[PDB]
Image 1: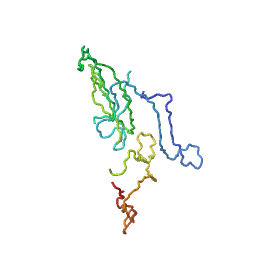
Image 2: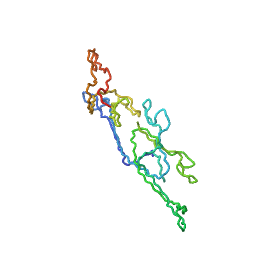
Image 3: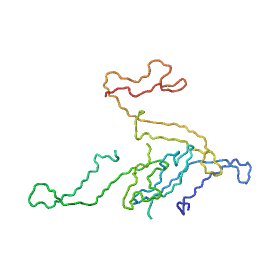
Length: 103
Length: 103
Length: 103
């Protein structure tokens, strides 16, 4: 309902965790689980590749269609770009449905 | 200068004419060229096929481009279509230069 | 106009950057982009090799030509060399056009 493709078998969840590294244990045995750990974080890069299959338009419509277009006139900043402060923003929502087809 | 492609050897001129059909000539010889002709016109169909080669866009531009689009809002008649009177008209001039490229 | 060789396809730009390494993130999730990073710089060596093709002189001129020459007489320091302070300097501009050729 929110939109999208519904799959019985969707891309699987990928779960990541830092393995625990204990701080020094006591020198005489205690059965309680360890609660003292070294403090850690991790950083890395991640890549996703997707192949999409397209369906081309086959229209016999004579006149031009509606198209998404960037604004013609001057503006303080560029839409879909950064700030003077380095903040990316997306100005509007963009849908998918510009071309037309008969029923 | 008006625009277009300039060719040393452009598509050749194609010339068409109705052949003359004389009305009845005089029954005794006269040397003067005939000036009496049957009245004729012709009609037919003509076909042109052209193959155009395209150059595709290779842009790395992040934000959307300008595009020619048909008007979004309601109107008395459809642009690039006929009248109630059957007259086709082209409402605006359309150029070629919407996408962008660096220098 | 500043001089040199003009190429449709010149040596490509080479871009280098240090990958970001985050400082420790917060322990409960926040959606905002990370703004705390470890401080880093990098150093290395870089090599360029170029092959140049030369055009040799073919002159029938009897008398000697002009040539770029280093100065004959004594001087406080050597031209195109370092300081007592270790600063390299280039004393004059050197052009390319000493030999002669007819028109």
